[PDB]
Amino acid sequence: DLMFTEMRAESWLRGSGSSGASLLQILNVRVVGSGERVVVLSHGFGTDQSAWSRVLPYLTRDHRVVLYDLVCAGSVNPDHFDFRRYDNLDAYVDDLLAILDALRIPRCAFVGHSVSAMIGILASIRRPDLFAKLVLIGASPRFLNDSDYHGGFELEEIQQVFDAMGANYSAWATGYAPLAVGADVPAAVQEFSRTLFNMRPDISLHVCQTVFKTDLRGVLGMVRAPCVVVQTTRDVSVPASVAAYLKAHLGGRTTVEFLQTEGHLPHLSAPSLLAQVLRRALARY
Amino acid sequence: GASLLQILNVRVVGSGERVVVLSHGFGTDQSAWSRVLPYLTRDHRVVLYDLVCAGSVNPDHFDFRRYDNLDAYVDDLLAILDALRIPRCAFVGHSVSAMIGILASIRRPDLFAKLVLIGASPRFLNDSDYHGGFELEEIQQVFDAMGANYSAWATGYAPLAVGADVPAAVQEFSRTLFNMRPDISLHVCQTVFKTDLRGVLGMVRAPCVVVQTTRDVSVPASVAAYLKAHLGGRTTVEFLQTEGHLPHLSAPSLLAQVLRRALARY
Ligand SMILES: CC1=C[C@H](O)OC1=O
C-alpha cells in the first residue's frame, strides 16, 4: 500500500538528524539475520559487540539481531564520549532508545550483559511497550555492599582499583582480564584483554565509576517485562545472593538460569553453553 | 536484488572517503577481522561480509553447482559493491579471498584501487616448475579425514593452520570451522585446490601489497616471491616476523599496523 510507504517516509524525516540516526554510525550499529522477532545484543564493560560473535550464528537464522557498541567502547570514536552527558546510566539508556527508534523497531527482546543489564532494566521501565522480554547476564542492581546488602565490593576496594587503573592502565588490564574471565579459558582472557586495552583509560575510569555508583534496587519492581536472569557459578563481580535478590525483586515474570560454568563473561568463555541458553530464552515472546 | 546484503551478513563500519573491503578465507567469517577493524574504522569506511560458505550464512543458499569455481564468489563480491553503490575501494583478502579479489580487479579494473593479499597463493598444488606446498595424494587424505569425522578433524587442523602458539587464535578458528557444514567445507576446500591463477596474474593492473608470514603451512616463502614477480601491477612484499597462515587471528597487534600503512593512501 502507498500509505505505508509515506508513513515510513515521514518518520525518516521526523527524526532525521537526532541523536539516534547519527548514532547508527557512531555506535557501529549492525543488523543481522532474518525473523520478525527482534533481538538486541548489548555488551558490557571492557568489551564491544565482537563479544557476541560466538553466539551470534546461533540466533541469526530465525531472529533479526541488532548489535551496537556502548559509547565507552574502544571501537567507538572517543571524542564522542561526553563526560558530562554520560554521568549516569540514564544517558546510555537514551542511546539505546534512540538507536531502536531510528531503526523503527516497536518491539524487541533485549539481551544485556552486566552494566547493559542495568541499562536494559531502566529502558524497560522507561518504555514498557518496547521490550517484550529481558535476558540479563552477569547482572546486579548494585555492586557496592550495603547495610543489609552484599554487593561484593567495598568502597575502599574500588578506590584501590581506580588507583591501579590510573597508575598504569595496560598493566592493570592484563592483570584484570583473567580474574574477570574467572575460568581457565585462555581465549576468553585474551579477547577480553584486547578490547580492554582498546579503551582510553579515562573513559574506563569514568564508566567504572558510573557503574559502581549505580543502585537500581529501588526500581526493580517497576519492570513489567518478563526476565530471564542468567547467573554463572562463581561470578567474581556478582555474588549468588545478588542474582537471588535481583530475581525476587523484578516485578515482571522472572526465571533464573544458573549456568554450570564459572566466570563473569560466559558469552566469551562459555559460548557453547550460552548459545543454547539464549535460543531457549528467545524462542517465544 | 541486494537481499544479498542480508544473505551474506554485509556490514559497513567507520567513516571516511576511502572505502576498504575486508574479505575472509576458508573456515572463518568476518569475525576474523574484529581485532584489527578498530584500527581502520576511524579514517576508513569498511565493508565486511561472509563468503557464501561461512558457517554464519544460511547453508540453503549454498548452490554446489553455481559455486563450482571462484567466478561465482567474485559475482557475489561485485554485486555487494554494486548494491552499496561503491565505485572504488581497496580490497583486503585472506587466502581464497586473495584469489577472489585478483579475479575481481581483472574483471572490474576501475573498482579496486589497491589490493592487499594475506596468506596468498595463485596455486596450492605443487607442479613441475612450481613449488606450491601441496600434493594430490595428501589432499585426498585430508578429504577422507574431513568426511570421516569432521569435528575431530577440525580440532586437529586448527592449531596447525594457526601455526603459532596463540591458543586464542586456535579457539576462534576452530569455532568457525565447526560452524561449517562438512559437505560445504569439502566442496570449498576442493574448489581452492583445483584453482590456478598463475595464468592471469600478469593481467592485474592494481598496485598490490603482498603480506607474507614466516612459516605458513599453506604458503611457501617462494610463493610470495612468485606472486611478487608475476602480478602485473606495482607490487611490494611485506614480511611479517610472525609465524602462521592467519595473522589477523594470531598477530593482530602486528597486522593492524601493516594494514594501516597499506591502506593510508590510494
Ligand atoms: C563489573 C565491573 C567491575 C569492573 O571494575 O568494572 C565493572 O563494570
Image (cartoon, coloured by chain):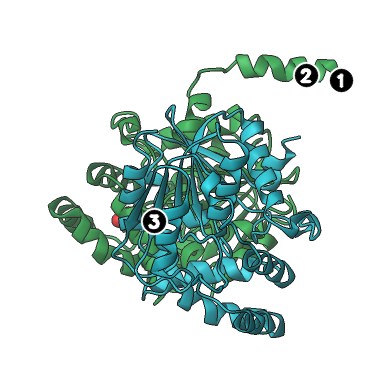
Chain colours: A green, B cyan
- Based on the displayed image, in which of its 4 quarters is residue A6 positioned? top right
Kind of residue at disc 2: Thr
Q: CA distance from mark 3 to mark 1?
A: 53 Å
- Based on the displayed image, in which of its 4 quarters is residue B176 positioned? bottom right
Furthest-right residue in this view: A1
Give the chain letter at badge 3. Answer: B
Q: CA distance from mark 2 to mark 3?
A: 48 Å
Does residue B146 appear in the picture of this structure? yes
Kind of residue at disc 3: Val
| Ligand 1 located in image quadrant | bottom left
Q: Position of residue A70 (x, y in %)?
A: 43, 42
**Residue lying at 32% horizontally and 61% vertically, measured from the top left:** B240
The tally of labels here is 3
B32 lies above or below A184: above
**Residue B211, numbered label:** 3
B41 lies above or below B99: above
Q: Which residue is mark 1?
A: A1
**Residue lying at 32% horizontally and 36% vertically, measured from the top left:** A78
Kind of residue at disc 1: Asp
Assess disc 1: are there few (<14), some (14-19) or many (≥20) residues with their C-alpha within 10 Å of its C-alpha: few
Assess disc 2: are there few (<14), some (14-19) or many (≥20) residues with their C-alpha within 10 Å of its C-alpha: few
Q: Position of residue A89 (x, y in %)?
A: 40, 39
Q: Is the C-beta separation of discs 3 and 1 under 8 Å? A: no
Q: Are labels 2 and 3 on one chain?
A: no
Q: Which residue is mark 2?
A: A5
Q: Is the C-beta separation of discs 1 and 2 under 8 Å? A: yes
Q: Nearer the viewer, mark 2 or mark 3?
A: 3
Q: Is residue A157 left or right of residue B96?
A: left
**Residue lying at 56% horizontally and 47% vertically, measured from the top left:** B101
Q: Is residue A181 left or right of residue A20?
A: left
